[PDB]
Image (tube, coloured by chain):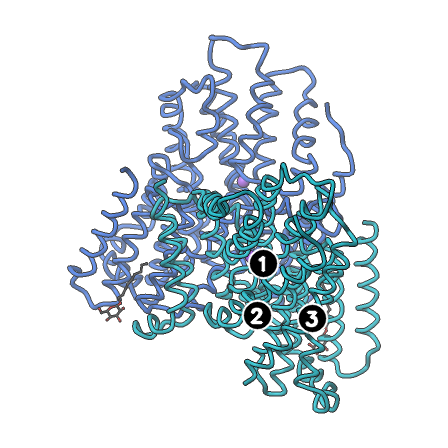
Chain colours: A cyan, B blue
Amino acid sequence: LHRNSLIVLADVALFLALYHFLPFEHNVVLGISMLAFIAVLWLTEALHVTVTAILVPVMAVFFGIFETQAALNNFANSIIFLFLGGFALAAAMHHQGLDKVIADKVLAMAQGKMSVAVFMLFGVTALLSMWISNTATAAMMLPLVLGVLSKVDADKQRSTYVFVLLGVAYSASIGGIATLVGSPPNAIAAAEVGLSFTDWMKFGLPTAMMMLPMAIAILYFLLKPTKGKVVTLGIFGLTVFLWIFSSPINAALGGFKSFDTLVALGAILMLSFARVVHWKEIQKTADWGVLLLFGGGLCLSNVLKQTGTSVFLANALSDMVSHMGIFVVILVVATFVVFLTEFASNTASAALLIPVFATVAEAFGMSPVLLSVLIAVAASCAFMLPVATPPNAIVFASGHIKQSEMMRVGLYLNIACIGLLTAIAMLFWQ
Amino acid sequence: HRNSLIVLADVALFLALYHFLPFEHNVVLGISMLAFIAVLWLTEALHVTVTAILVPVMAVFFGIFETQAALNNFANSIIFLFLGGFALAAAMHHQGLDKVIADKVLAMAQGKMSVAVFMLFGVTALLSMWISNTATAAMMLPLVLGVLSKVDADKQRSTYVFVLLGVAYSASIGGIATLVGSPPNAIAAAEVGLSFTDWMKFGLPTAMMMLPMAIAILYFLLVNWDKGKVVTLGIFGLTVFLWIFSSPINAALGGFKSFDTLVALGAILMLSFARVVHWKEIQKTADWGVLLLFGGGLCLSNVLKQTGTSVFLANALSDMVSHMGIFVVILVVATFVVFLTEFASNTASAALLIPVFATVAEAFGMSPVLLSVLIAVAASCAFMLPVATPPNAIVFASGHIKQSEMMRVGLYLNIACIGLLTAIAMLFWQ
Ligand SMILES: CCCCCCCCCO[C@@H]1O[C@H](CO)[C@@H](O)[C@H](O)[C@H]1O
Ligand SMILES: CCCCCCCCCO[C@@H]1O[C@H](CO)[C@@H](O)[C@H](O)[C@H]1O
Ligand code: NA
Ligand code: NA
């Protein structure tokens, strides 16, 4: 506060302002004033991300857009649960100390000292993050990353943090795509368009395994150089096997309608029956307010719809768009890759935009998928400043940080991103 | 290997029932499931929350429901109202509104002891109606063991008699009386469609009789601040004003459909707008596994209704009860309040029994309410051995040698109530 406290107030004014004049049509007035109002709180963060989320539904309902239980049922949506057991799988894989060994194992696999070790770290960050979490994975990775440079002290110069520490934060964010879980933007794409685990994986996984080298290499030239729980490991693999091949498997049992969730809910089940994780540790590791957030953004979408806003937008958007894209259109949306670097919460960014862009592509009768993936894949591309995203913050503390060296470097990457994404987006468009 | 084996038995029992039960199919499933489930919730070999996730998963694999529609139960509007509760308390604790209400009421008795212990009971009950029990208990403990210091005596009771039981029990009696804390009361209102103000119509005057009674039978047998936490109290009061008056307010609006959920939800706003409590705190405070349990439990009441196991059981007991009750029923249903207690688990108990009793009572052409209320209130009547409830299990340090002492003192209490619930419940027959 009082900043945040007033901003809300400013935003209430903004709403009342739009709501009361903005003549248009009443139910579009609603959608817009609401759209804008929520557009603010989630950008910045004037309230907490999760609060505004819980704000969304009560604002439908009152205003009569929905009825309480229907507005609420948004939270029960299946991807949320897919995500929930994503968390569970991590939580277990942590508390049994599986990740600890992975790094200890792959790092030490580097044999001697430094040279290769650094890159090892990068991969293990990306691989590990694929599954666990960005910040979490970055945080955990950081202390091992300091250990690798000790006799590597180097008042001169860049290796200690610039590169390796900065590399890590970046790897942490890159393999954050590549899997529907996590980070949460992927989840929110998936919720919106109804992607399967492997559906999303088809896109991210490769985009990730290119953007990674591209990033580290860009990074390189602008700097440089100098135990019984296998059950967990196995339960992990089966759950992931079940996810990839979900299609034939589900096909082959009949049904099943959102298999990937049952596969996931199926993990927490086998994990807790196998006695390899306690629910306390699930409940802690689980970010309950992202799951809450998912539903917020789902409710938003249905608001944009019932209200008529999502169609109105596309109407007004029409003449303009028919002239430009899709190649200019996706260059341009992919240019909100620059936009997760300013106040982000890539989550809250994704939370805001995907509903808007997917549900307009719907009144144009194209697939909400392309934009919805891209927007989400772009939001994870946040580099160039702490913060967000937090892995940046994580690395920014301690040894020879930069603050303008992030700034420089993150610019050449963020661009080779906006380029690389536009590139791929175009290919899958064939 | 303990628990895991109990699980195997539970699976062995299921396969038995599934293959050998001689009725239709849907009933074979329904019964089969009501059994395996019940076995797992009573005991707890799975945890609980794990069990609750299981309800939906079976239900969709046996085709009873489709994935979402099953999952949609998790988002029922009462879970949110209970989340509401959790934040209201997340806040009043974070601020110290609990300690203050406690300290200032307690110390108010000036000269110590006699008035001061009874001071303690009223406070613990007040603090419970809103916050929690386990929470409210562990909080009262130190404050209790301090109040009794000057008498450290091996002579004798006055800790293990009036203090620690009178404390632990006051938590539980205050457990009732409001929809928020502990969960059974929610579970009931959840299934039979009760408002905050309805459930108090019963629960409150029930906990007011009951506290003195638990205190009487327990006798004859066995600095301060005030900071800006004042706003919290204002918010709290206001929330409780709308909750009480929800009825005439709502209709002076129209709708609104689950107004009390809105009211609760709005509380989460007012609180976090007033910069009085963070999400970090609401999240750490809330018991997500209960919220989760709430839903999966609901999924189960729905499994009964559908598979027609509800009328199976209803028709099954048709002769026994039609010539038996009602009186005998309620006396009997209540007297299963000796249940909890042994092997206990006050929540998980009510989580099995309400769906069951509620949905039969419907099958009989009877308002679900009265029974389901009774079952919850009863569910909180845990005295004699710990656990459950945990309040019991808390107060064991020091005069904890009580052991039998509880068992003894508690037996009268248990029965005392078997008469009391049966009285009120019959008078409520109007
Ligand atoms: C926490 C925020 C509380 C906001 C409550 C404001 C409610 C105002 C009602 O709007 C209504 O919308 C309808 C269309 O949907 C119109 O038909 C109707 O004429 C109009 O009255
Ligand atoms: C993680 C625990 C979940 C495991 C549950 C597996 C249940 C599969 C059985 O389905 C049932 O089989 C019958 C024939 O065999 C069919 O007639 C019927 O349609 C169908 O209801
Ligand atoms: Na991640
Ligand atoms: Na309580």
Does label 1 point to a residue whose CB lies under 8 Å from ligand 1?
no
- Report the Cα–Cα distance between label 1 and label 2: 15 Å
Instruction: Nearest to the eye among marks 3 and 1: give it.
Output: 1
Residue density around tag 1, few if under 14, some if 14–19, many if 20 or more, within 10 Å: some
Q: Please state which of residues A70 and B157 is positioned toward the viewer in this rendering.
A: A70
Amino acid at pointer 3: Phe
Q: Residue at x 28, y 37 (%)?
A: B2
Quadrant in which residue B359 is drawn: bottom left
> What's the chain of the residue with tag 1?
A
Q: According to the image, label 2 marks what residue?
A: A189
- Lower sequence index among marks 3 and 1: 3
The quarter in which the N terminus of chain B is drawn is: top left
Q: Is the C-beta separation of discs 1 and 2 under 8 Å?
A: no
Please state the total of marks drawn on the protein image: 3
Residue A290 percent across, percent down from the top left = 59, 57
Q: Position of residue B420 (x, y in %)?
A: 42, 38
Q: In terms of sequence position, does the residue under pointer 2 or pointer 3 come before the other?
A: 3
Q: Identify which amino acid the numbered label 1 is placed on.
A: Leu
Residue at 28% in and 60% down: B314
Residue B278 to residue A22: above or below? above
What residue sits right under mark 1 in the picture?
A292
- How far is mark 2 from mark 3, CA to CA? 27 Å
Disc sitting over residue A365 in the figure: none
From the viewer's side, name the closer residue of B366 and B50.
B50
What is the crowding at mark 3: few (fewer than 14 residues within 10 Å), some, or many (at least 20)?
Answer: few
Picture disc at residue A63: 3
Question: Are both tags, 1 and 2, on one chain?
Answer: yes
From the viewer's side, name the closer residue of B275 and B319. Answer: B275
**In-front residue for pair A212/A353:** A212
Specify the subunit that label 3 lies on.
A
Q: Secondary structure at mark 1?
A: helix
Q: Residue at x 16, y 63 (%)?
A: B22
